[PDB]
Length: 207
Ligand SMILES: Cn1nc(-c2ccccc2)cc1Nc1cc(O)cc(O)c1C(=O)N1Cc2cccnc2C1
Image (cartoon, rainbow, N blue to C red; front, top):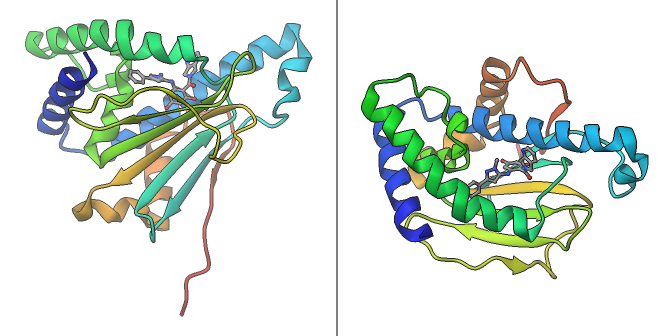
């Protein structure tokens, strides 16, 4: 399942999307939807925000690690949610994505096919997904092109409280996406619509 699908999408997405910066639009869009979900659930059950009071998106580059992390305090995913994403959604969305592609239809927005996650492959050679839903444990899953990694209970990672954290291991020739000014421009250009705070961690540079 996952090995073939991730390999296909890695090839197709890198071939047809020359503007690699849209990966950040897709991730921010997914985070925004997850935040809409917990916001709406908290209307009828305020205690849903007990795990994490604030709703936001935070971007954390780590140049020493070569990673760009996008974390949100959205509703998160149960293990069943993540399993469904990896199985049913990935298979069906890949089919719809490449029929749209073949059709010559406007496929600019990848997430309309439910596989926007894989646009991470524009800039990343592997992604570590950490996620925490109020009804389940914290889980981690690793994605790489051709990879068959198992969803695992995360016992040694930092606690999310609630939400989802996408840690992207940036490609060697694309470290520009770790730079503060480049990230800010991309966010400004592609995320005007978002109604949640978008935060960036900037670190004093030696020097
Ligand atoms: C959209 N999506 N797709 C995959 C996927 C993974 C592998 C293979 C195929 C698909 C995973 C996700 N979830 C997320 C991706 C993010 O970047 C940020 C997030 O906060 C989530 C999240 O926790 N959400 C819960 C939720 C509830 C209601 C509406 N939207 C959401 C999104």
